[PDB]
Image (cartoon, rainbow, N blue to C red):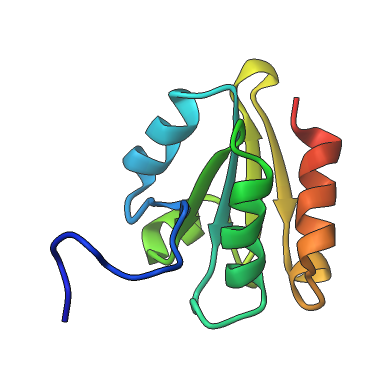
Length: 116
């Protein structure tokens, strides 16, 4: 309903839309630390928790995707959240074992743990 100025209170910053594998790896390659929420559904607790961690980790590259090709490239099979750290080229896969009961604390934690 709105696409111009004054969108309404509530925004700040949201995770990037990596609808493609190249764009995903690009946003990750264009930054030291990158956190991305590979979800098959943007209605799970993980989504709000990620969009929230975004403001908790500005330095970290906030990202999010729902594309099959991407969720496939990262072998995502459970609304997994992957933290790629360009520097050491690491990739932490916060899968279902952590997505089923994911919490803003957890996401922000795992990140705070591997935000290298």
